[PDB]
Length: 128
Ligand SMILES: [Zn+2]
Image (cartoon, rainbow, N blue to C red; front, side):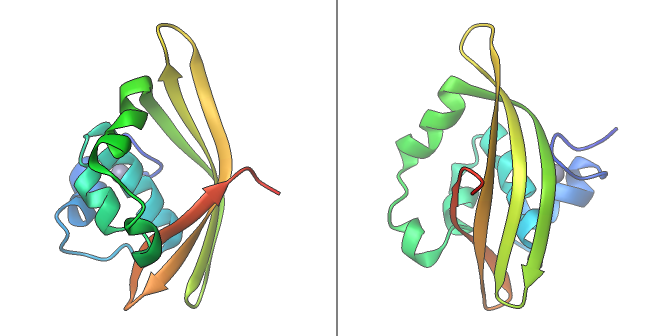
């Protein structure tokens, strides 16, 4: 019994404290794979909350849903990650079934901003 996200953990022991909004991930990767689970659980509310203060204004309820509507999240596979005081960076691959049949994998590197000890998603794009 393992979590549906990059964590050798259960659902509760892993994503639970994050989705409960009770405990801070304290790590860029720890935040990322927990948010990934929220996408699969359509808890886009959690997503927005743990998004960068600047980027959070850019988010929308339906748009946040739009991704899961077309991309069925199968598995999350982290490649690398690093916390640097207040700046974080994580390279990953998100494997999802996009459409009726094809499994597509989104490989990119997301930067995270640390605010008040909590991690917030700043942005992510193709690995440079
Ligand atoms: Zn998890």
